[PDB]
Length: 46
Length: 45
Image 1 (cartoon, helix red, strand yellow):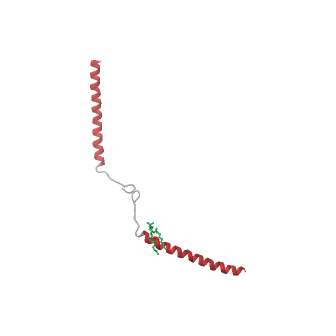
Image 2: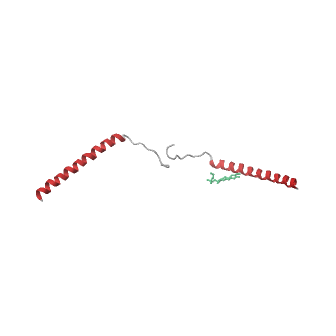
Image 3: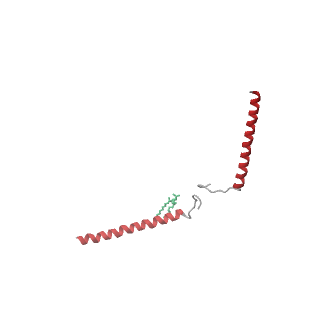
């Protein structure tokens, strides 16, 4: 490409909405897994 | 034009060749007119 070329993405807004949906659900699964992990490690130490 | 575009000139080499000729000849015309300034100031002054 000579110098800098402008390029345009297809459906960027819809892709952002689904990205937010996947990230937020993925982050919740991190909290749920962490909560269960600490629950077991609370009992194991106790 | 978005960002910087590349453009290509038509016959750049032939145009440079003819540019030197016109510049060089006009330099000769300057010297000739200076000579007429000297042969006319020697006669008068």
